[PDB]
Length: 129
Ligand SMILES: Cc1cn([C@H]2C[C@H](OP(=O)(O)O)[C@@H](COP(=O)(O)O)O2)c(=O)[nH]c1=O
Ligand SMILES: [Ca+2]
Image (cartoon, rainbow, N blue to C red; front, side):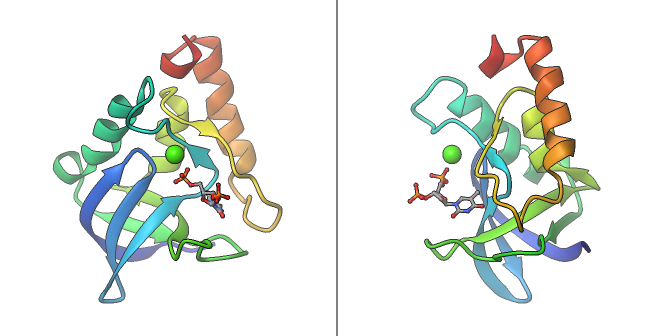
């Protein structure tokens, strides 16, 4: 896999971000993760965590996996990095998302994320509390 530049337009919630990608606006849904909806426990927390990338980071990059690049809603499907840190991984590590939506073909970072989830679970963090 390879990382490509993009520009943050708006972080929407915990696992959805709108980016300018090759000059066109696209809503990206983060691969392999599920944050609570905003109306559920830890939804607001995950939303603020991801939103914080606007203030807390400088360089945003997208990395597609080897399978489908768009979902049936027209959203991009990718791993998103902020100053080199994977947002997907960070959300799972903090117990703000669960590993989810795992499809063969788009699961390159599955084991990486499951490691993060196991730590967050052991610590009884947030979702796991
Ligand atoms: C992360 C991911 C989500 N999705 C789709 C399936 C879910 O739609 P359905 O329930 O209609 O199948 C939806 C979950 O998105 P949200 O978690 O953003 O609501 O996104 C994919 O199709 N592939 C993916 O890799
Ligand atoms: Ca969600």
